[PDB]
Image (cartoon, helix red, strand yellow):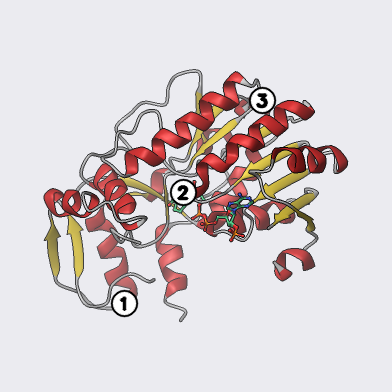
Amino acid sequence: GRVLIAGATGFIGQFVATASLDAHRPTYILARFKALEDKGAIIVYGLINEQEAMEKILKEHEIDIVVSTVGGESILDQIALVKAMKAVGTIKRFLPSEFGHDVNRADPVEPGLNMYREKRRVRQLVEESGIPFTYICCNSIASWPYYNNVLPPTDFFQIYGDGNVKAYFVAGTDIGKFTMKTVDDVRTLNKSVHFRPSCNCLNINELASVWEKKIGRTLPRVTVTEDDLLAAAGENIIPQSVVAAFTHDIFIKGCQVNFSIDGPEDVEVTTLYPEDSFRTVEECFGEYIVK
Ligand SMILES: NC(=O)C1=CN([C@@H]2O[C@H](COP(=O)(O)OP(=O)(O)OC[C@H]3O[C@@H](n4cnc5c(N)ncnc54)[C@H](OP(=O)(O)O)[C@@H]3O)[C@@H](O)[C@H]2O)C=CC1
């Protein structure tokens, strides 16, 4: 199947585009990069918010799989993309711009809640339009989780709340690799795919300690309270306050870990692809040290 990726120069999109090419999939990358092209990508021109233009591309290039990685501020640009895929009727799988939490289960404060409102709206449209779908709920990219946003700190650690709430951290390269595995898997059709690598389930205190090992010394630790984060969210400064709201949901409320994925509409990456190891946080934090 031919893959079209929208947002391939984006933060997440670069990993997904690169993984697709590595897997020897025919990959088309939508342009409003040199490394992408050298690796085999075909560049096509347009914007996902122009319905007619998208219908043309999907038809002319015989696209089977569409993956959108547009940013938090462009979620509703996908509305015209969904109408376009419904029109051409030949799409075998659509992955919207999801790449985070389960937007149905999580309940962040504003203004994070508005972004989830928009992603839910796109899901409703996808499902009513009968387009086959996969929702990538891949939790947190493996990084230092700065409340407003590279590298982890070298002065002091800001620890949210008790620093004892677990989250899942996934290498950008693993986000890409495992995402592309799902696009034509029978087991991920019309499912949410959750990324729960058991070795990468860490709290902020454990993240700090991993980093302390890498830098060969300790830093003081200071508390950033729940109210500190809610005050930052309450400023409604975009996109910083959005990240503050998500930080509160993850590290104060436990949103990544506080639900079962046992039901028929949820699958989990490590059980789908057994004996296929995720990179560790130790490993990722090791490559920052090469700078
Ligand atoms: N799990 C995690 O830790 C994280 C997850 N997220 C999620 O990942 C998703 C991707 O966001 P992130 O990588 O920051 O996105 P970026 O802002 O880094 O990249 C967005 C990409 O979308 C392209 N784009 C935007 N609008 C259009 C359009 N109308 N038509 C065609 N292309 C368009 C942009 O192109 P251009 O530059 O030309 O405008 C850009 O290449 C979001 O849903 C976000 O919520 C993102 C970061 C952290």
- The residue sitting at 66% across, 37% down in the picture is 81
Quadrant where the N terminus sits is top right
Q: Residues within 10 Å of mark 2 (few under 14, many from 20)?
A: some
Q: Amino acid at mark 1?
A: Ile
- Secondary element type, mark 3: loop
- State the mark number for residue 72: 2
Residue at mark 2: C-beta within 8 A of ligand 1:
yes
Give residue 126's position: percent from left, percent from top.
Answer: 59, 27
- Secondary element type, mark 2: helix
- Give how far apart the Cα atoms at labels 2 and 1 are: 33 Å
Give the vertical position of 218 relative to 31 (above or below). below
| In this rendering, position of residue 178 left or right of residue 157 | right
Camera-near label (3 vs 1) is 3
Label 3: which residue?
131
Q: Amino acid at mark 3?
A: Ile
Label 1: which residue?
215
